[PDB]
Image: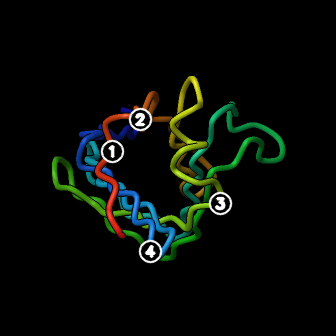
Amino acid sequence: ENLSFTVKTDRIVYDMTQQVITIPVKPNKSVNASDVHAVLTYGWDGNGSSEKVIGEVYLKDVQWTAGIEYTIMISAELSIDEIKSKDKVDLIVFYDGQMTITENLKPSSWTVVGP
């Protein structure tokens, strides 16, 4: 069965001070991946070169445990106001040559902190 992630969108945090987005993902199965690339986008199917990037991170030797939250941290390349202006925010997770898309992260619901 294909790996997928669910996200409780109101637990996503946009930190204004560090310009960092923290995303707790819950995998549906346990998978260990050598090389992972997570891309936050407002419009990309995950094919070819990346488009409409809100931010991205490269990770090594990731251990996902089914049903247990895993925290991805992404440097924000668009302000939170601009992110909330978008129609749809997706997270694309690449892992050892495969990919999965968690759709509709609903930035209106995100916790936003920092003075």
The residue pinned by badge 3 equals: 77
* Earlier residue among tags 1 and 4: 4
Identify the residue under disc 4: 17
Quote the CA–CA distance across marks 3 and 2.
16 Å
Q: Nearer the viewer, mark 3 or mark 2?
A: 3
Picture residue at 61% right of the left edge, 43% below the top: 82
Write down the residue under mark 1: 110
Disc sitting over residue 105 in the figure: 2
Where disc 3 sits, the SS reads: loop
Q: For residue 44, which quarter of the picture?
A: top right
Q: For label 1, count other residues whose C-alpha is less than 10 Å away and answer few (under 14), some (14-19) or many (20+).
A: many
Q: CA distance from mark 4 to mark 3?
A: 13 Å
- Location of residue 111 in the rendering, given as x and y in whole percent from the top left corner: 29, 51
Quarter of the image where one finds residue 57: bottom right
Can you tell which of label 4 and label 2 is closer to the viewer?
A: 4
Residue drawn at point x = 43 percent, y = 67 percent: 73
Decide: marks 2, 1 in contact (CB < 8 A)? yes
Please say if 108 is above or below 17: above
Mark 1 vs mark 4, CA separation in Å: 15 Å
**In the image, what residue type sits under mark 2?**
Leu
Determine whether label 4 and label 3 are within 8 Å by CB.
Answer: no
Q: Are marks 4 and 2 in contact (CB under 8 Å)?
A: no
Residue 66, image x and y in percent?
20, 49
Q: Of helix, strand and loop, which one carries label 4?
A: loop
Measure the alpha-carbon separation of dots 2 and 1.
Answer: 9 Å
Residue 69 rendering spot, x and y as whole percentages: 21, 56
The quarter of the picture where the N terminus appears is top left
Q: Which of the two discs, 4 and 2, labels the residue nearer the N terminus?
A: 4
**Could you say where residue 26 lies in the image, as x and y percent from the top left?**
25, 47
